[PDB]
Image (tube, rainbow over all chains, first blue to last red):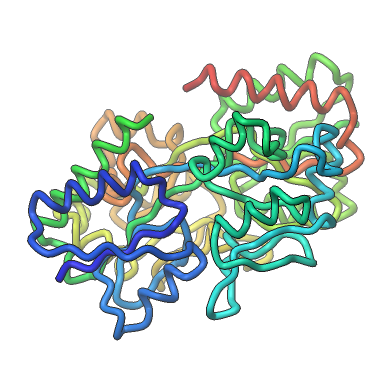
Length: 203
Length: 203
């Protein structure tokens, strides 16, 4: 009934929050997961009937939907600890556009500026697990959500190459594309203000 | 000698910081101001010889420059207190793309997705002062940096229409496009880490 989509860069905390809050005013809620490189294509397929989509991907105006922001999440470009581009860093951040990158692929073979790769050439994968399996072998470097790569980082399996580009991790807004019918529904504003208020408790 | 460009959305605090820190390792520093809708075009004109550019505008790869992020700044969509789209808000955020907008114009008549207007039609101006003079008359709504519009807000001259889109103000990364020669110059990394460290003291 209420069909909500949540991309894969959305940390499970952010998902738990969304879900629990929907659960206040909603009676049937379906929670679809998706790659961030297919979220926006998916909601566009009218037959998919997505009422709400929670994604890091950005596009100006989608047809039937409006956009706002729920919060912020972080991501790191990572690599194998003995990747050439480790440590040595100033010039290295430029050299990413040479070294090979493991990118998230889309069914529409298409990519926003936000998720377009930064280097030719690239190896595409469908999901973060496959990104990092590769990236753990030395096969490329990737961009990955904080949570997907926290553990591995502490355990020294992976290094971060992103600190000079943006110390602390790469920030990105988490967006809510919501079917326009929902604008001016009390349940939806309740969810919005609720989920939001709570996502500030995380940080 | 060191020619640094700073757009007009960069709060004067952020500028003071940049300037003072450059002043540590630099002996001649020229500080050029620019609209955020001309920063990137300007650095591209090879004859302008901009070594560093501090701007909110985003572009993937400029030719001779690299990109990183220095911090974050905030902006609000504002209007006259009795603008139609005041108060009443859920549906209203959608209706911006109808109501008339006062946008920042570019010499190249061209605009990034970041600064493209969101509604046809629009009135262009060259600068924030002219934006708000207009917007204070009821002539349109605009998007404006926090600092440019703080005072007016407290004084009730202007209302914010942006809170449901993103509570607290609209976040945007402040970017440093820096001539590639500067990568691996000690003075430049000193500045980077310095300016950066200090911009966290603001918030």
